[PDB]
Length: 150
Image 1 (cartoon, rainbow, N blue to C red):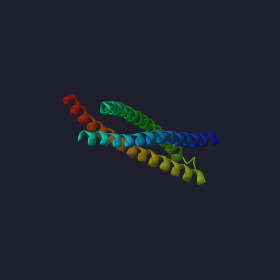
Image 2 (image 1 turned 90 degrees about the horizontal axis):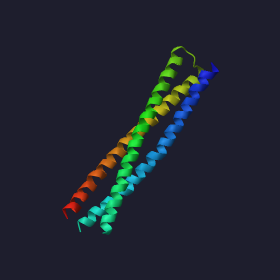
Image 3 (image 1 turned 120 degrees about the vertical axis):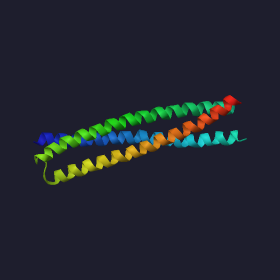
Image 4 (image 1 turned 135 degrees about the vertical axis):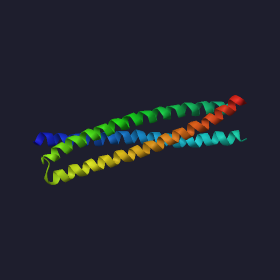
């Protein structure tokens, strides 16, 4: 009835807000990774040549924070996908019996496809974030070994 259809539309909106909130944090993490890449490059060029130690300590902290941010993003991404999947089953069930029709059926189907595509794009963005933090972890480890050595 009007109420279950109302419920699907509200859930589709709730999910759309969760993707929105996840995108803010993902973008922020991505921007931190980029500034940190630049900072590690500087340390690397300089070692090719105590302020150095403070910069390396600051970078290492900043790297560990980003890794923790990426793990939060990974967990929330899983929560978002699970909600998408629950909505797919509910929508699918009402559709099987025909209880969504007219412009609403096309619009709810289109919205399911929109949210799925955005969630999959965020998953790709997240894979790139993971890739980035693993690169920076390997480069700072090289620097730490050199310092221990010297």
